[PDB]
Amino acid sequence: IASTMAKDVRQFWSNVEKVVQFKQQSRLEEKRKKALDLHLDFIVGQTEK
Amino acid sequence: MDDDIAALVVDNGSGMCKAGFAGDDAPRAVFPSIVGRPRHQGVMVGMGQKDSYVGDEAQSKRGILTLKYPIEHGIVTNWDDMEKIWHHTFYNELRVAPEEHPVLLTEAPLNPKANREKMTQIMFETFNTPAMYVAIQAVLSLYASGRTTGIVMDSGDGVTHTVPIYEGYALPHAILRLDLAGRDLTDYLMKILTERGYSFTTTAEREIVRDIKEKLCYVALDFEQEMATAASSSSLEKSYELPDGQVITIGNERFRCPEALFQPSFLGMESCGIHETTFNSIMKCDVDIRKDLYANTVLSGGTTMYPGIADRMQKEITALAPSTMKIKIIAPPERKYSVWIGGSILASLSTFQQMWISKQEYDESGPSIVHRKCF
Image 1 (cartoon, rainbow over the protein chains, first blue to last red):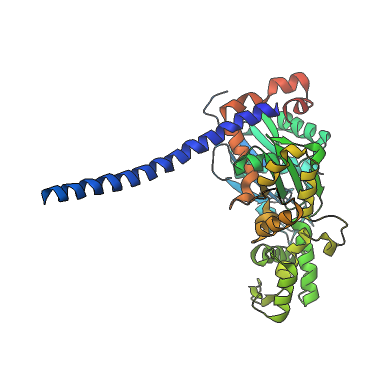
Image 2: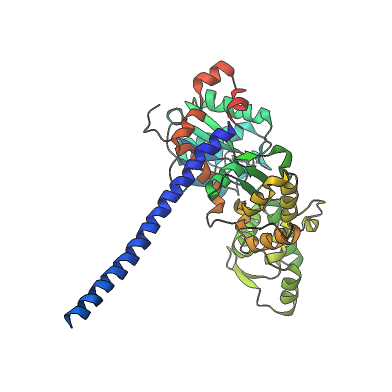
């Protein structure tokens, strides 16, 4: 019984990981936007010279 | 059962009762677990004479009511007052019908079987609840902390327990109990304040001293160094305003009071401290899981809300535990509500729907079904 309940509540920590996936996506976006946009602007400004 | 009916969680605390709905982030009701009765007949002429009062209603009328605690050291000693407290929680605090929602109850570790059977009988016969379940407070605290394996040092208002848990298994052979909680700490604070010149004798003065404890007391990392600093400097003193406007000064009593948790000798008790208790509890377990028990040490209960208690526990368990073990104390900011949080969590899981004790199972097997469904 208690092993079943432990395995059942183990799903709550996979859910906590699914939540942390939200922070992971936030960081991924905040970094990818910055990097890619800055590099695009820089290379465009370098080619227009 | 309709999937839209949320289950009820009721944390049966010795000092404070917490109740709410499954899925909510915090309990909707938190009131003292007390029942007051008029001292003399005729004192409440015109104020709606009630045969008894519960919660804050009785707390505010302590001057004219005789208050009793149905829960002593985490064990129910008066079932009539406990039924009154449950009726209150259901009808006045939550304002719901218990026969329409499952009720999840919390119990201290090593609860007598008779008490579990009586709780089941009360819930199935008096309130006619459709289903219920009983869970250990430390297990819910751990399930709220973020782990399934570890040891929980739950210190409430009436009793403290060290429950080692591996994969949700509260190991009975390794559970240790210590009759030292916020109540004895408040008594010791009253004593040491009387030693300082502030005499508190009445029950309302006891609540004043309890508030002083909860507001100003803290756990020192080094008791001897803190005592030396207090004796050599007054920077550790704090002022407190009494209800009558008088301002008092609390000195070393801030950290001398909670020190009893680590050195019960101050209370004349021949028992080991909370840190030594946790160490011994971890030692009674298999060596294969002591690593996880040390790495998943969790703190719960209102008494564990003292600032700096986590650092002191870390220091003590690191000094006591082997050098090869990594000690980690877990003290969530809301650890005072971890019990109810874990209860709501467990009640909100779909896989847990098969764990409820239904009215049919109770009628077929009786109160003893708790011993077959609740572990």
